Image 1 (spheres, rainbow, N blue to C red):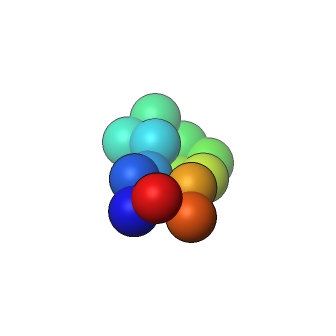
Image 2 (image 1 turned 180 degrees about the horizontal axis):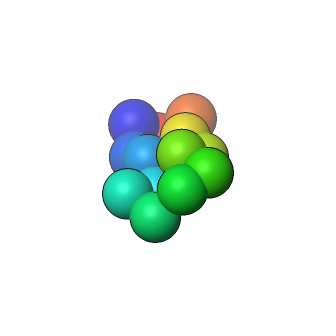
Image 3 (image 1 turned 135 degrees about the vertical axis):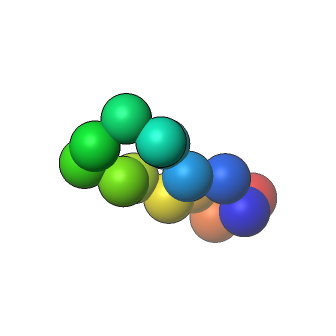
Length: 14
């Protein structure tokens, strides 16, 4: 449950 704000938005399963 975490996403990069810097694009591309890569979201992690946490």
